[PDB]
Image: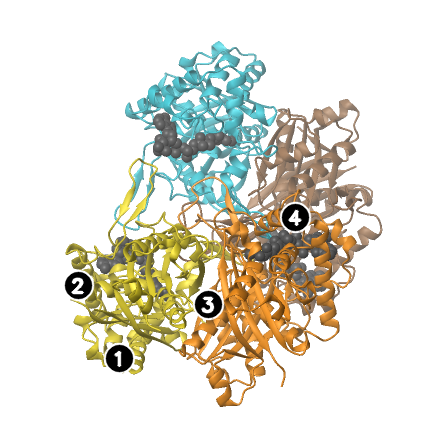
Chain colours: A yellow, B orange, C brown, D cyan
Amino acid sequence: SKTVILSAARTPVGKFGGSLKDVKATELGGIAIKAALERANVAASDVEEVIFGTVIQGGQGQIPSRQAARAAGIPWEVQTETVNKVCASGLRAVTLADQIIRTGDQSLIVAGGMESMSNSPYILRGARWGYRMGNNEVIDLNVADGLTCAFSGTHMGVYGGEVAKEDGISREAQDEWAYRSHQRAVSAHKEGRFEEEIVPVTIPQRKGDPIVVAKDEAPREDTTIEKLAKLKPVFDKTATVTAGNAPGLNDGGAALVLMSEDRAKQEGRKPLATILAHTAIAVESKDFPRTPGYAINALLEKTGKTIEDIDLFEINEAFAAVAIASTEIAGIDPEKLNVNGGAVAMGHPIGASGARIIVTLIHALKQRGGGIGIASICSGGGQGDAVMIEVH
Amino acid sequence: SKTVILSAARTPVGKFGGSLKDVKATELGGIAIKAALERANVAASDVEEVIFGTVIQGGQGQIPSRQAARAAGIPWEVQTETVNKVCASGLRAVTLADQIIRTGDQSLIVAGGMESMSNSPYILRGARWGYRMGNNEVIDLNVADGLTCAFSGTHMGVYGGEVAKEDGISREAQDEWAYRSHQRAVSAHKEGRFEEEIVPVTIPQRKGDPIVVAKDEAPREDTTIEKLAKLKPVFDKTATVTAGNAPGLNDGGAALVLMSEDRAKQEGRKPLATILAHTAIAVESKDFPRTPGYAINALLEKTGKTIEDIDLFEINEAFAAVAIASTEIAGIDPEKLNVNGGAVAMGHPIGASGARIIVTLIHALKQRGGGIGIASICSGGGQGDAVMIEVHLE
Amino acid sequence: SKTVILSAARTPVGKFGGSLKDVKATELGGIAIKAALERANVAASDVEEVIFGTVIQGGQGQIPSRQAARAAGIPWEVQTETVNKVCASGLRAVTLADQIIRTGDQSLIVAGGMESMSNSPYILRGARWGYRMGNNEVIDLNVADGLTCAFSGTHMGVYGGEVAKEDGISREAQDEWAYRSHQRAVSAHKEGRFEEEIVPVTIPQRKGDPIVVAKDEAPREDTTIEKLAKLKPVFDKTATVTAGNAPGLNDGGAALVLMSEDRAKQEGRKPLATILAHTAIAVESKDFPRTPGYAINALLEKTGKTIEDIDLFEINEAFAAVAIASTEIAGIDPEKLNVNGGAVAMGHPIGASGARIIVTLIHALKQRGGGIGIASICSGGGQGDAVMIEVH
Amino acid sequence: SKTVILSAARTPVGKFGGSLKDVKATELGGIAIKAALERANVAASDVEEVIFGTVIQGGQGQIPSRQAARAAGIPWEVQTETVNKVCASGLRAVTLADQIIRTGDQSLIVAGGMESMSNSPYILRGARWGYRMGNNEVIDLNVADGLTCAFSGTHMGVYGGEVAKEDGISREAQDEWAYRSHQRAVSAHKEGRFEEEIVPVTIPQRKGDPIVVAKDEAPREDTTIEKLAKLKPVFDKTATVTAGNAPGLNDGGAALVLMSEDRAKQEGRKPLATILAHTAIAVESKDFPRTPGYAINALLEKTGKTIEDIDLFEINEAFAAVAIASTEIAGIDPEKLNVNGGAVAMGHPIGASGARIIVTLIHALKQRGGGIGIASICSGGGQGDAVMIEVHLE
Ligand SMILES: CC(C)(COP(=O)(O)OP(=O)(O)OC[C@H]1O[C@@H](n2cnc3c(N)ncnc32)[C@H](O)[C@@H]1OP(=O)(O)O)[C@@H](O)C(=O)NCCC(=O)NCCS
Ligand SMILES: CC(C)(COP(=O)(O)OP(=O)(O)OC[C@H]1O[C@@H](n2cnc3c(N)ncnc32)[C@H](O)[C@@H]1OP(=O)(O)O)[C@@H](O)C(=O)NCCC(=O)NCCS
Ligand SMILES: CC(C)(COP(=O)(O)OP(=O)(O)OC[C@H]1O[C@@H](n2cnc3c(N)ncnc32)[C@H](O)[C@@H]1OP(=O)(O)O)[C@@H](O)C(=O)NCCC(=O)NCCS
Ligand SMILES: CC(C)(COP(=O)(O)OP(=O)(O)OC[C@H]1O[C@@H](n2cnc3c(N)ncnc32)[C@H](O)[C@@H]1OP(=O)(O)O)[C@@H](O)C(=O)NCCC(=O)NCCS
């Protein structure tokens, strides 16, 4: 009952309708999974279970995790489940893998997440039994299943703005975090700090030569405080949340290979990282933006560690407001937060983001010579999940 | 040691466009969960995790398990995830609850599943970035995400007929198993053997009093071998699979309350059942109908145990052909299989069926004076899952 | 330059999603056309032109008039146009035929109208070039092309209520007209006064025996002033227009055979009726309910006839309010108006109604021993058309 | 006696999804109508009737002719009807105006047509009363109402290739006529021969200054026989019809002002042109491409006249194959046919094309010093319409 991470791989994150528009979510997951197995030196046929997150499942076909496992070359004989915990899906896949391995039921699991918000369909409610008369709506499945509360219909972006308002986080503080997120992502890319974690995506072409996507699409070298201050409130004209200080709709895949500490020892494998612990909390839907600091505090209490014991943090930038608020709630030095950039700059491919931030955290830790990291992520519907990892 | 089941409840199963047409999947889940908590005498605010299965998630809204949890009165502070393992979703929700409780991370979980195949939407692929010109498809999401192979586009019912053909199971054997399934379900309803497991669904009317649905809609009192032999093959003129020896599209929910052995003893709680063990196997998509007997064989191998120690079996009737094939492959006595009816009579609300068969198995064990049971279910994509349970009275 | 009517035939009028739900508009038009040719004793091959009205053309296929001509057994060699003047379509087809015959360019035209509001599709605007993101609408083509003003988006039923309000026509007066319209339609049917004009519709069956529709579906023997007074305002909670005092959405076909007076004389044909004259007026969209009395007054001025010279009137019951208002504006004895019932009782299959009221007027005239009739009809967009016919 | 044309105006023709993408059909109609009234020096409030053609009416809203009339500034008090005779709609609008004026019922009519094939919607058949289960079609309304036979479902382009095959018109003859069509259209634009007939379209931008579209978008300066020979057949691997020797889907409007001879003389108005005569014929749907030459022959027979008395012809290029076939059938000198280009180069906005070719014919006659012309157009469903006009200067 201890879980090691042998490997951690992610695709670049694409913009909505951008570089990965013609790649299915399951293909992005397959690419991440295959790169993780290569980097782990694990044969596909030795995988015992695949646990894969994706949120907008409508129209992906039967059990998307199986499609991603098969796209990776994992044989038919390996069992799989698809999991949905909205933004936490990719992280919960990993913490579920940790739990299953700690029972001894399995010793080698692939876990991660995938999303192609570019390829989400539109739906027709009412067409099955008939509209009869009067106009009806054609519903963006990203909006219906990902971006709006199932209880109130309110957009996540309205809840983000309401929390920023109640927490007293200014427009100017949010635009400063957005700027810093862009500058750290462009810097990390230029200086080669994403080279190790990224598996490029090759897109067969109508033309002759294949398109290679090797870089995160959304970071802007040319964004500035001045340009961000010009943008308009997107969800409410009185709020502070804009397109510039909120993450986009995005496409991406992320995968990790997990193994029992005991099996890795016996096989003579040097793990990339160890899972020390994880916890989740839940609050009302409208308070989802508050959860990452609560989840971090809950995990510190669980482990008996203090904030000063943590070398780096990845808090998913659900909004810039959420990185700032969660910094206050947990008393985090922002110099140790999202040091290679975060979702405001890099995007939020919902089902992948939870696994993506672990992949980024591991490599950020390796880059500063190892240490202890927490990845924390809030999720629509009002949950927060956090995991503590060690890179030796 | 062994995870305990305090309670197990299911809705009636409705026909497609039938008696539960106007009830959302998440409401069916909530009703089942609330009845499970009432029967367990567990407070909703003491639940630590809800793990709920559903397959056609398209258009249900954010994290359907959470909607089901809230519909049951479970507070905001309880964590939840939705799981999808096609037909196995409701069963894998339970075996995941078992693994989590066995780690010690939690001691009280609600697990189960739900589906409203009636309320699944249609989709438009291509409308987001534009058709430009030419006709396109408006796609039935039950067909796209539930009933067709992600790899080949082939209907599960084609795979059902192909496996029945290859195993040499006749049209006549399939129709006899279908007639038997209806006789056993009708018989279980009329003799009061479903009364304990079913939580009725109350549908508030715009008009007069509420409608209360208390009975499984699909079982037919008046079906016969004669009528079944008249039906035409549905997926291939040359195959043996009809609307009468294949389950329907259906609406339902089912829920169980799971607790650690240790916590159950501290609180004075007698288990309804114990989870002994579970396993899963996986094969090619086209071979999904063969998995239940293989899942049983691997589960027996794992527990050192013998087919003769098992008092009752629930094998989800993915087709009549699957109950027959699995009987030979596991060497099962048919008199010990699906004794109150199965999916051919009762229906297959995909996300719920894996929890549903465990609820039916627990109550069939209890009616028999107790014993050991295996629930086994195959799922689209080529998986089989089986769980071994123990039921004792007093 | 005079036009005779050799024959006049209509299908029964079906309710929305009712008796004619599985018959295409072009099939309803074909059935009417074929019955008119039989009743005229005119060979299909001698027809020189088919002019046919239909309003909701979306999804009917290429030139619906040609489909109706071919469904009637009219050979490929006969020319055809489809015309759209909303509610006036079926009447304008007839008055256009009169004009063409008065030039001598042709001497034998089939004219009429057809509508299947049951079979109108739904549309997606935005799907061609792509929604990109956000919910959109699926639009009822009856609502978009038939029932709402192209300028304001307002429902015809809102304009009906606004005119009833401005003209001081009470809820109670409208419910009395609705009751009278139902009682005259049921009476006409029971006493055989629709037997001559109706051509039954035969619907081939999944079962063995074909369904024969021989009766107008919408008239209610059991409707009463009491039941009508219980109904709620449908378009605005402060207005007087209800489901009971406004016509429905309906399905129907109507056809007439027109011939030059000179050719009919030479062939020894006794015409059913003669077209004496016609006129149209136009007003702003919102004033469409006012046009029938104006059109009648314009036609009396044109012919130098007075209201007392007219034996019977058919004013299409666009609303009960419109029969009442148009009665005042033209000073019409209501005992000579819509004597066998009208659209409030019988339905308003938009593209057919203009031809339908002429078919009804001719037979109502024959039943009282001949005389002079005016048919008048308002049409969405703010037009009114009226025709004066003689039955000798 | 003879109806007179005071004026004739057309928009540029836009490509599908091209330069007029953001302009509704009714706006294109209004722009053409307003330019016709300006050029006729006729007051909008003196018009007595608007007869306007459009084919894909689905989703345009109530009586599109009235929307076009109001877009032109024509008052509410002017009567209007929309007509549909597929590709002949714009031309039959004019010949109907001619018949009405010849009765004396009216003395001043606006006639013409419009289409925005760019803005045609998709439809859902079956969503009103419900799919129940199974995939359905989302239908391109251009395809359903414009481009396919109501009787067979066959694309007009299949009928085009079948008639080209049966008439023995080679791929090479079709591509030479296509190259010629582009050369003549490009040439007419560059040499200022379209400047008089075209009314530019001004598209107000959300952003900076308005976009002014003044040029036909489809004519290609850089097309060659070589490039045309490289294209693959569109509707049948074995046919000769390509994207290059068939017209596109296009956006456009065109309008004419018609007046009685008597009224024109009272008001001092010199006619742009006189309508001499018109006729229409009808054949089987599949034979629609053969009708233009037959319509010309019947119109000559009717007027006692001879093919040699006609100075210019506009035969709508429904396909290159149709211009060639019709040339043989009517015995036309190609040097007198479509002399400023036709639909293969210029496009086919179905509802407008029949008015458009009359506008182009009037200005080609005027450029030639005057004369007699015939416009002939075939239409989906199997019709042909031809109109004879006279143009004199001074
Ligand atoms: C906020 C949101 C509505 C924006 O959608 P969008 O309008 O498509 O966003 P875009 O990036 O296309 O548009 C924003 C505009 O601001 C500009 N902009 C955005 N970020 C900028 C930056 N950092 N610097 C400068 N300009 C910027 C863009 O260039 C664009 O302007 P343009 O139209 O001239 O190109 C969408 O990304 C969203 O809903 N995000 C939240 C996702 C979420 O909540 N996920 C979790 C769900 S549980
Ligand atoms: C088989 C299937 C296509 C049938 O759909 P359907 O046509 O809507 O089925 P119905 O329930 O309407 O039955 C069709 C006919 O058979 C008849 N029939 C069905 N079962 C019968 C029985 N036991 N006795 C007599 N008649 C019976 C019905 O009465 C009906 O007759 P009717 O149309 O005259 O009323 C559909 O249920 C299916 O695809 N099921 C497979 C489920 C599955 O594979 N799920 C797992 C995938 S991962
Ligand atoms: C008014 C309108 C919205 C009604 O649509 P609808 O709701 O489908 O109408 P229905 O007849 O189904 O419903 C009306 C209700 O009143 C009742 N009702 C209607 N007429 C009645 C009568 N004469 N006596 C008693 N009850 C009557 C019906 O039974 C029904 O009640 P129910 O739901 O219990 O069956 C629709 O017919 C309409 O828009 N009409 C105007 C058409 C028009 O303007 N055409 C010209 C366009 S240019
Ligand atoms: C023929 C038809 C299917 C073509 O549609 P499409 O594929 O959208 O056509 P495009 O304009 O995109 O042309 C296709 C290709 O041919 C090329 N092409 C077309 N005309 C060309 C020319 N003159 N020279 C060189 N290349 C040419 C285009 O550049 C394009 O190449 P690309 O795809 O690499 O850019 C369509 O226009 C049609 O159905 N037309 C018939 C109209 C009709 O029948 N109307 C009357 C019915 S009642």
Mark 2 — on which chain does it sit? Answer: A
Residue identified by numbered label 1 = A329
Asked if badge 4 and badge 2 are on a common chain, one would say no
Badge 1 density bin: few <14, some 14–19, many ≥20, Cα 10 Å:
some
Q: Is residue B155 visible?
A: yes
Labels 2 and 3 positioned on one and the same chain = no
Q: Which residue is mark 2?
A: A367
Question: Which residue in the structure is indicated by mark 4?
Answer: B168
Q: Nearer the viewer, mark 4 or mark 2?
A: 4
Mark 1–mark 2 distance (CA, rounded to whole Å)? 27 Å
The residue under label 3 is: B82
> Mark 1 or mark 2, which is nearer to you?
2
Do pointers 1 and 2 mark residues of a single chain? Answer: yes
Q: Residues within 10 Å of mark 2 (few under 14, many from 20)?
A: few
Q: Amino acid at mark 3?
A: Thr
Chain that bears disc 3: B
Q: Secondary structure at mark 3?
A: strand
The secondary element bearing badge 2 is classed as helix
Viewer-closest of D224 and D15: D224
In the image, residue D17 lies at what x, y percent? 38, 40
Q: Is mark 4 within 8 Å of ligand 2?
A: no
Please tell me whether mark 3 or mark 1 is closer to you in this view. 3
Residues at marks 3 and 1, CA–CA distance in whole angstroms: 29 Å
- Ligand 2 lies in quarter: bottom right
Point 30% across, 48% down: residue: D205
Q: Are marks 3 and 4 on the same chain?
A: yes
The residue under label 1 is which amino acid type?
Answer: Ile
Graded by Cα atoms within 10 Å as few (under 14), some (14 to 19) or many (20 or more), the crowding at tag 4 reads few
Q: Earlier in the sequence, mark 3 or mark 4?
A: 3
* Closer-to-camera residue (B218/C12): B218
Question: Of tags 3 and 4, which is closer to the observer?
Answer: 4
